Every structure is written in C-alpha cells, then in structure tokens.
Length: 80
Image (cartoon, rainbow, N blue to C red; front, side, top):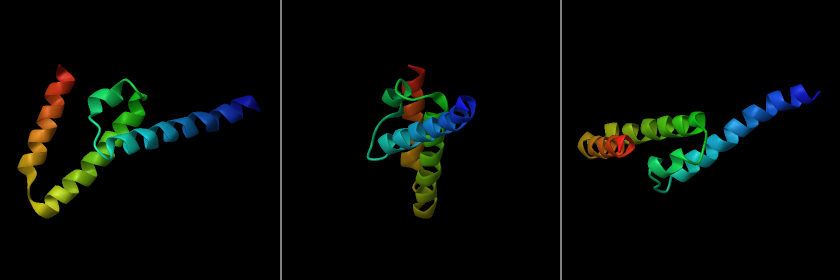
C-alpha cells in the first residue's frame, strides 16, 4: 500500500518541482540560482522547455544573435 503511494508520490513531486522551476525561470530568473533549488531532472526539463519556446520565437523573428549571446553567457556563468 505505501509502496504504491510512494510510486505515485515521487512522480507528483518531480512534476511539482518541474512546474515550480519553470515558473521561476519564467519572468526572468538565471539558471545559476535555480540549480541549488531543485532536483536535476526538474531544472533540466524547465531549461529545455524554455529553450524550445525562446528559440521558436527567435526562429519566427530571426534574431538568433541575441539569444546565442545570452546562452553563451549562461554557459560561461555555469562553468564559473
């Protein structure tokens, strides 16, 4: 009984952390601060969803330069 409760609870917790992390990333929040806040899977999925949405709007606007510089800055900050 409690194993079957836990099997659903882990997935619910992962989804909750994912939506909280994506919500934080939305409205403007650097990934560096969020790394120490949520599990790896949640921040990973939130980052990937954001990247898809942002690059889709970049593709419709054809302004890849600004977003590429932003992502490069994110990578340098994460490396630091």
